Each structure stands twice: as C-alpha cells, then as structure tokens.
Image (cartoon, one colour):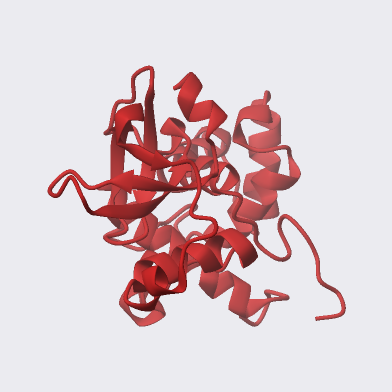
Length: 220
C-alpha cells in the first residue's frame, strides 16, 4: 500500500497463482477504486490484462515492475501482453476492458466517439469490480448523462476537491435538469459516489484520460 503508491499506474508482470512458472501483465491501480477488495502493506491492487479482473497481490508475486524489453518470441503468442505493451506506450485501453456499446443499450457531445469509449470502459469496469450497472442510471427523473457528470466534477477539481453542497447543486443544474428541489445537491453527490467515483479513482491512477475532459486535441 505504500508499495501500492510507489507502483501506481505501472504496467507490471505478475506471477500466476495457478502456475508458478507462468505470469500475466497487470496494471497497478488505486485501492480507492474498489471497495470489495482489501489491500494491506506490501500488497498492490492490479487489473489483469488477461481476464480484466482485479486482484490484490503481494510483493513476492511481482515478477517485474515493468514489461519492458521483452523478446519478440514472448509477445508473438501472448495477445494480452501485446495489449499491455500498447497500453504502456500509447494508452489504448484493450477491447476486453470495454463493454460493447450495444450491450449498454451524440447530438450534444463534441466528441461522441470519446463519449462511447468512456461509457464502454465505465460499464466494463463496473462489471469487473462487481457493482455492475444493471439499469440505466437516473437523476432528476431523467436518464443520467454519465460522461457529462464526470466532466462537470472534473472541472470542479474532482470529487474529493468538492467541499460545498452548493457546488453539487450547481453541477445538478449544469446537467440540464430543469427542476431543483432541496435534495438535488445530496442526490447528485450520491449518484456520483455510486456510479462514477470508483471509476474516477481508477482512471486517474491508471493514467487514463478522455478528450474534452482532461485534455483537448483541436487539430485531430
């Protein structure tokens, strides 16, 4: 856990639990993204590039703190390791960390592709963590625009930087919900904590960023 902090966001090589000679590539992420797994000292929370699942691992199972300089023969028959190498170099999130946009189910979003990317990653993350999104989330008796909420909270400094119910009330208004009662502030805070806070912690510690939220590519 101080070990977790030292290795945060690294793509690492993990000894397999079922075969002491095999290994798998994994991404070190914040324990704050998963409430259902506990992480002690000299343990790390990782997400597997093989099965997309989360595991708490001890220092003895960290074969390498990186996947650098591996031989071409190693990658030739290891699609998980190819995907992990792409993640390290260019931050392309693997397909198996994404849910199909159809299994989840653009006029206002400036980057509707990035919005879909965001949603596919959030839904797969939520499933793999064990808090899957079964019903379309709702806020103010209307489907919740998850990407927009994420953006609004980011521009306020992230969930943990929000110190006022009045900030949350204005986020609720900035979502375009037309009727505000006295519970609006508490309702959007609670909805954020339920659907997005874990994903915020995960993406930040994973070094995953979205266009039109974290950065801008005007000439793309």
